[PDB]
Image (cartoon, rainbow, N blue to C red; front, side, top):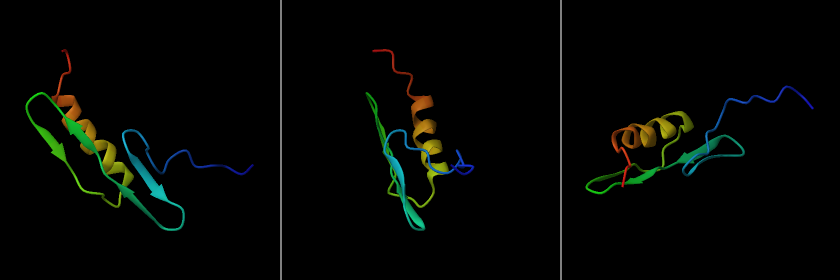
Length: 62
């Protein structure tokens, strides 16, 4: 049990890196008017930032 780095990938909506030296990240957010769709990127950080950016704007309240 070596010091496992808790910082690397962020699998929230649909983000997951690859075991080797890569990783795809694509988020999907649909609202009651508009929706954004970003293609699979190569960074898990920007991934959560993208989905969150749109989500924060879409105040879901029925």
